[PDB]
Amino acid sequence: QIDLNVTCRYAGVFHVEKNGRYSISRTEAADLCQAFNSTLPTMDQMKLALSKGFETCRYGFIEGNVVIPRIHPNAICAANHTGVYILVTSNTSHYDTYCFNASAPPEEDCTSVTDLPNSFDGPVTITIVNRDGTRYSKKGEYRTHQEDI
Image (cartoon, rainbow, N blue to C red):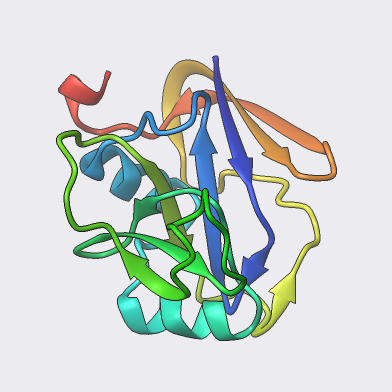
């Protein structure tokens, strides 16, 4: 069973938490985004997302780096840095992910995500979990690297 918690989209950019916080690899992140018909964001898209009001208190993959977008300074979220803060030093490889959907509205889309459109045949119950609690489930798979499984 896999629970994927999603935020609102901002300029098409959203945060995905898979079950436990920080349990996704780089290769899984890419696979996951792919299941949403999305891609790992470029820095520039992430900068745009941020300027429209996107912030989280969780580190996550983009294309090339691990980042956390911050608008409002906070002691436990990136130590009061603001902007798209790049993670510099870490021992470990697992974080959350950000994904980018080019088809999303240009601003805040807080409507509910109701499908993992591009997931493939598999045995896992995959549940998408919105912040307002609304859920969509399907039996399938999205991971293409065996070590991720």
